Length: 227
Length: 227
Ligand SMILES: CC(C)(c1ccc(O)cc1)c1ccc(O)cc1
Ligand SMILES: CC(C)(c1ccc(O)cc1)c1ccc(O)cc1
Figure 1 (cartoon, rainbow over the protein chains, first blue to last red):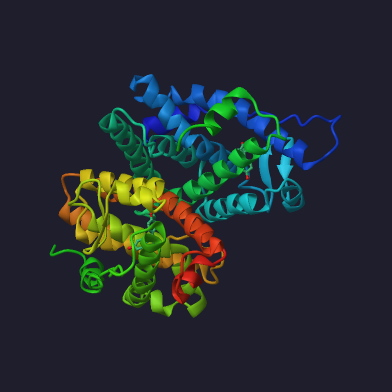
Figure 2 (figure 1 turned 60 degrees about the vertical axis):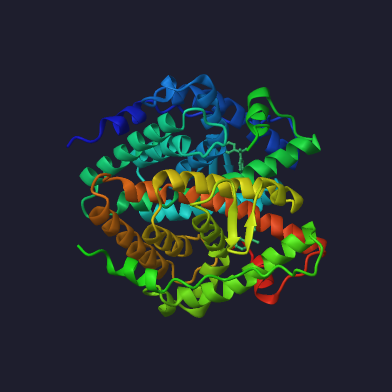
């Protein structure tokens, strides 16, 4: 009852912080903000792919299934990260230590409604006192449970889901005896994450079509996935 | 260990079957199909409002909170119903006993992608052997967990969520000892339901804007909710 090994493992597999590095020579605009954010996402996607390899059983899936899970889950993983980084803040989203968006900035970027939904995720997790252990486990569950239409080995993916769910259940049983239903409460946060991700993918797909915001190869690869 | 009372109660509160009654004098078209479906939804929404009153604690919320939960959850409740009605069928959606859509009909109605996602929900629940007891409990959880941005009494809504989650957990502990993680598996089906609902609301909102498909008052009320 030092806690669950999978949880411990995900904690040490957690990537280091990444800076956004908005270009200080460029005038502030919606284009600058969206460019900065998509550039940051592209770099994060590299680290997310590397991170996934540490999840027990993930690297044993076919390359096609690994890619399918990542192409369905990437936005949820990105959003859960900004959510977690923002828990100790008030009405602000910490995309990076050097890129914190308040309401005015979100409006300027055309992201008021989307960032408000992300702040809704933040609000609920603040009330629940979301722990880092729970965050990393939920990121892994979101990956495994992402509902790609293209899975080859359905049973192996369900097995991965079960392994990660078990880890969450075991963690909560040991760490949160005061609330025997806390694991389920955690799982019940996933629908809002999925809802927000679905809308964010459509939003940025539309930005891609408009062609005014430069996007890098990996971000585009994820955005152009069939979902 | 005759099972959970809330589950038993939801089972007897289950509304009776409703027929679609497509107009046999009208030529088949996309407009006919969509008209028929939205008409059916309108009638179902009446029965769903009545049904919600049977859920322990729901009628004790403010009228505003009851409406907020229903306006966020209605599409999920409707979709979970067609999903459940379709479990014993193959690649067909049983909107009603007299309205069963196959792939060609979905294409004709402009609903291929949406109905395919609903069939994805069906596929997963068939594999899990979803029971009526679990269906009705999930409908109630979807209502309570619908993530409206407009809730007045956040704590009372979280209490309702907990009561219903407890019922699911208790049901599974008694009925499914072979799988100590089945309740969580059930909760993990909710993200796809939310994803599909989010897309369906947008789809039918766009049909509303186009103005070619007649819609009744209650369906419109739900569709025009701020979400
Ligand atoms: C994908 C997006 C550019 C992003 C970038 C980086 C990040 O850490 C999280 C999310 C994003 C999505 C939704 C949103 O409202 C703002 C930004
Ligand atoms: C809301 C909709 C008209 C409906 C009507 C009735 C129903 O039982 C379930 C869903 C609907 C949603 C999504 C969809 O693909 C088809 C029909």
